[PDB]
Image (cartoon, rainbow, N blue to C red; front, side, top):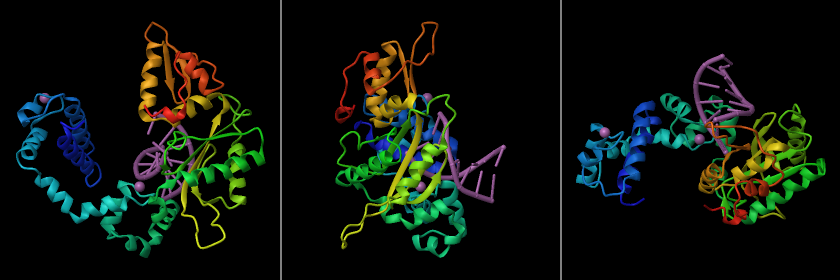
Length: 327
DNA sequence: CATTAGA
DNA sequence: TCTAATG
Ligand SMILES: [Cs+]
Ligand SMILES: [Cs+]
C-alpha cells in the first residue's frame, strides 16, 4: 500500500504504456500481474533479486526494479514520458469515442492535437464528434448540488410517461458522494423481466420523453436496453448555462433490479466484501441474481428479490444504508 | 463482460 | 462478421 509504492507505480506506468502506445498485450499483461504480486508482498523490496523470487517476476522486470531502486528513476520511463508520439496517444485517448486503436491511427495520420481533430471532423464518427464537441464539459466533475437537480427531472418525466416505472440513480451519487463523473439511471418496469420478451419501447419511451423536454441533447448510442447520451440542466434566467453531462440509462427486467441496483451502487469493495460473505453464508451474488450454493461444488436457483433488503436478509447481514456502503 | 456502432 | 469503445 506504500512500502511497495514506487514499484507498483512505475510498474503500472510500464504496463499502461505497452498496452496503448504499443500493442504488447502480453508485456502489458506481464507488468500487471507483477505489479499485482509485488503489491501484496509484505516487506520492502530491497533489490531485484528479492522481487525476483516472486511469481511473474522475471529477469526483465527485476532488472527494472533495481534501476528504480538504485536511482530514483528509470530511463525507459523517462524516455516514454518524453516521447511525443506516445504522449499524443495518451492525450487523444481522453476524447470520448477514442480508444487506443483509434488514437494510433489518428496519430499515424498526423492528428495529434485538439485542433488537429477539429480540422478533420470528417475522419471522426458520431461518438467521437460529440466527445470532441464536449471535451471540456466531459472532463468536468458533476456537483451533487447538480445531480440532485438532474435526478429531479429524471424521475419526473419517468413518472409522467408511465407511473409503473422505477428509476434509481445508482453510483457514488447513490452513496453520498460530493460529486460525480456522470449520471447513471437504472431502469425497470414490471411488465419487463427475465422471460417477458422485451418491450424496447419501455426504454424508447423514456428517452423520447427526456428529449422532448430538452434534458437529453445528444445520443452517443441507443440500443434496446441501454441508452448512452448527453444532458443539460436548463440554463436558468441567463448568465449561467450548464455544462454538457454524460448520462446513461438502462433497461432491466423488474426481476433483477435490486441486485443490479446493489451492485452498481458499490463501492467496488463493499461489493466484493458483501459478495465474499454471501459465499460463507451459502450464496452467490452477481449483478443479476443470488443463488444458493450446493455443496457438490456449485449450484443455481435464483432467489426472489423485492428489495435491497432481501439480498441482505438472505446472507443474514446488516442492512447498510447506501451512505455507508463505502466498504 | 455485455451491449452498441460500424464498416 | 469482427472489432472497437463504454461501463
Ligand atoms: Cs519467479
Ligand atoms: Cs476515451
